[PDB]
Length: 42
DNA sequence: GTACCTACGGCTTATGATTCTTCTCGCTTCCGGCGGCATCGGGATGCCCGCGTTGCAGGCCA
Image (cartoon, rainbow, N blue to C red; front, side, top):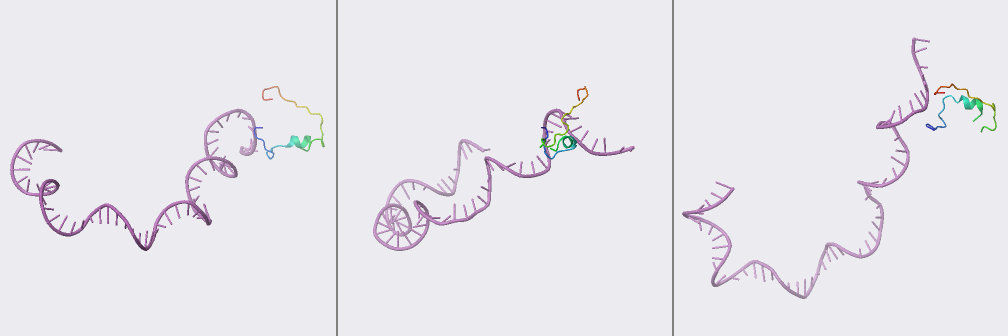
């Protein structure tokens, strides 16, 4: 929301690897889990 | 031995949009010059008489 741009991209690895970016075709990795540290930055 | 990314917040500066200033197209139509003729009020010219202009000398003012 702070900077919305369809061209702005740095990694793009997550969306490229989970789906094709639209998603009903490729539904690979139906189960995802996000492990994160217990600090405030986590 | 060294390089490149963003979040947390504020002012600015680097560029596409809207109200105020200005540059001047259209001719046409009611209106404003423009000329001629009868008209009328002023005045220049002449004569008479008293008042406006000026020189002299004194008392007042800047």
